[PDB]
Image 1: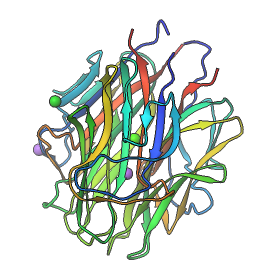
Image 2: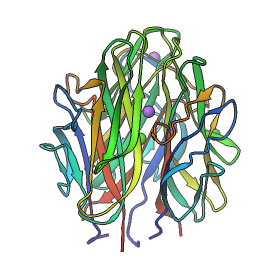
Image 3: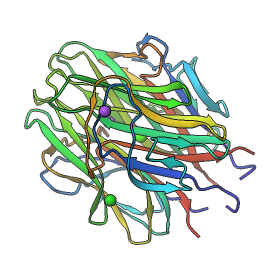
Image 4: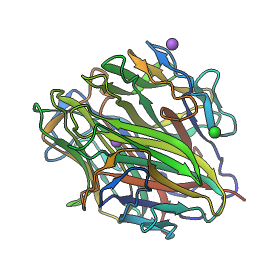
Length: 136
Length: 136
Length: 133
Ligand SMILES: [Ca+2]
Ligand SMILES: [Cl-]
Ligand code: NA
Ligand code: NA
């Protein structure tokens, strides 16, 4: 309908990450409005409203048994997940959120311990989201 | 647009909970329209339409047996997620659905073979969903 | 506002490099998903969400790969793995711009996918988020 904002993004992870750092998904497939920045890993809200996000982060198979990944809004964790495998086999840390955001809010995925697989261009580890409703 | 139904929720889980009747996600982050009730663990439809739901449940079961988390619509399973590990008690059970619902329908998560854990921040086990289209 | 959305589960075992034919169809608004091919075919330009959750078969192998493809190109990859040949899932999600005729589907890239019968363990769903003009 006229006036509905179109805001959506989807990016994969080319480079491996470990420890406690923000995941800079840099294989950008969709980025309507350029509100996702692959140089920072952050989606920045431009319109107050209700947003969906999801993430799938592949643990570094063959090199460790656990890896944690959090979805953050500004300075707060809003979703958490753990990948774990006693044989160091591949496993995912994945979760999804629905959040109200205000302009300037940042949403991003941060590692919270362990090692993440670096996918080159294969998009094994991903971050995506979109606006569901704009506030009146 | 203004006037169109805005219905969306997201909830985590405080501490560890059995869910063999219903898993009552009780850390409610988003509940636009208040169609999710943390005291019953159910999302109740009030508008005919198409709805998305997803869940990510961190479960702990007995050594070496399968466990599962089912998304139910009324008395029917509409998705399931199964996990089994040889000597790892904690694993995720996650799935996603798109469902047509009528007023009165109840959508919720039920567990078997293990207990759900919210982790320290309540955000490791989650349930979310929203209306995609309203029947008109 | 166009209404296009689907959701289906995998009844039968698949293996190797074949397309996954999710044939336990729960939702298929607009009839744009074909359970006999496993493919969603775009009918109007726009922005679409898809997600999949594919269960690896137990007791016959330790790895399985399942990739979401757009036309003949991988747009998301996933691996399931369990060294004791127990279950594991290969899952991912995407947001894609599509044009009419574009096909979106899940294809194996090695390994065996569990045939769930009516259990809806292994799933594929999607919907249009915004239509183009
Ligand atoms: Ca999802
Ligand atoms: Cl590419
Ligand atoms: Na690093
Ligand atoms: Na899954």
